[PDB]
Length: 337
Length: 230
Ligand SMILES: Nc1ncnc2c1ncn2[C@@H]1O[C@H](COP(=O)(O)OP(=O)(O)OP(O)(O)=S)[C@@H](O)[C@H]1O
Ligand SMILES: [Cl-]
Ligand SMILES: [Mg+2]
Ligand SMILES: [Mg+2]
Ligand SMILES: [Zn+2]
Image (tube, rainbow over all chains, first blue to last red; front, side, top):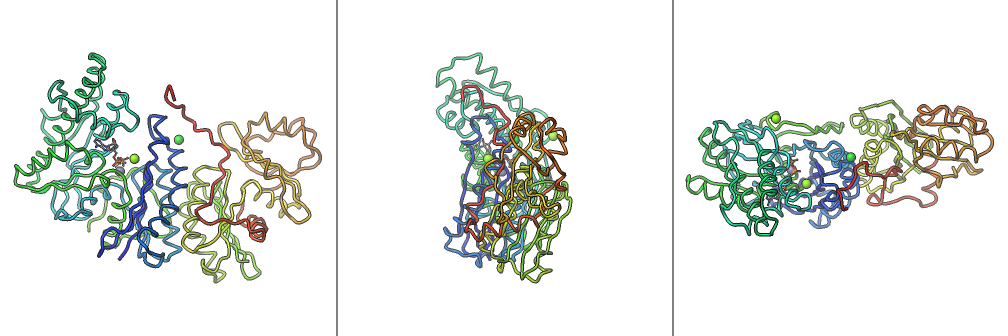
């Protein structure tokens, strides 16, 4: 079959078409980062307005890309939450009404389940069970995954998510919002070990995270040192190394707790070069396996929604005629499949 | 000449269908429930008159102004339907729609339409029906402070009917204006009243492909200041 997936949860409009035989047939994306940069954060009303401008044109482009017509589509999946209510509503209203007009099922998709299943789009996808580390702008969670919709929350950040931590320190370094990826580029030129950040919540037991204290440590380090490019790169590297070391320690403890041999990483921060290398190295030493999405499917995109939509449709999940969005929607509450 | 109209730009939710020489319509107050009601209502009105979406000649939608969220629900639903069935779309002003409603209910041919825009402002228009039933005055649509509306009214003459929640918010809007004001008996737009406007635009070739549909928000100021230096 073929599913059209629609993602409008925050500031990316992503549309994709996934065929369960031939794989991904189309993938279209518009990122609004330039629209929000001048404000230092996503402005919900501007985000909502721009999804209206992009959603239909990118669906039209997706069909053209794939060389498909309306009749080739078997279901429409759309992100229903979590996310920004105004942004979710655009993709969800377009999606549900399109499905009605095409007389195909409409599949409401959980945004984080989309992230979690993104590594399934690659060759050699993970088998159950696995530990999943979801690390994005607003989420940082460890999950025990024993099957589709069988997600047990093991731990989560009690403050800043890893992604927002990257963005806040990047802002302190004078980078444009969201500066996470650019901080990582700076870090690549940094001298290992010149500064040393703490690894919060690693001295105590448990699987929860905290990153807010790293913004403070960064701020104080920045103001107490010189402003030359090398020093700034050294600060970026010490920050990145501390976040990565913290995530690795927590992943290790999750693998210990569950007994699992597979670790899946997803969400925007899973695009991080240092994190990908360090978790791969860890899994090699454990004689286990790591799994991640291609870098462009780590951050928000439509491909993961088309895929998760296909999985959910096959599990019997469809929408009635109501358009329901859920801006806060815990992953652990999804029905098993 | 089969036209389906939908609207969710205000606290109301409504759909209407002109098909086979009859008009069917449904209107209800749906505060906070638009997303749960709109597609069931579309399905219901279509099924009732035995019409398929792909047999529709044009899809009319409430383009705004109104609630930013509601305007977007309306255009989003309309876009999905129009994309799905390859329908041309006709955007209809919520302000003109209420003018048409005042005419239907009271015979009013000159209408001062005001919508409570929040933030101490109103969406405003001055609409006047010509001999052919076309509402002139679209160029007057604006978001305005009540004081500015009051100044504007002193430049108008004669008898007008008032419609919209802007008058609910500011019933003293026209104090000392010198106009003769009648109640237009319309607080919210109804899809039924979009139909004659849509039929005029259809005949004039003033429809658009789904990718060209645009909301009319009127208020376009961001409500957040840019960072220092931008
Ligand atoms: N190479 C990178 N290194 C570190 N962080 C990155 C990198 N690439 C992206 N990010 C961060 O990933 C975050 C965005 O990830 P996304 O999955 O797109 O976020 P999001 O969907 O808005 O967050 P949610 O709603 O909580 S899943 C941002 O904070 C980015 O800074
Ligand atoms: Cl906003
Ligand atoms: Mg984003
Ligand atoms: Mg908490
Ligand atoms: Zn995301």
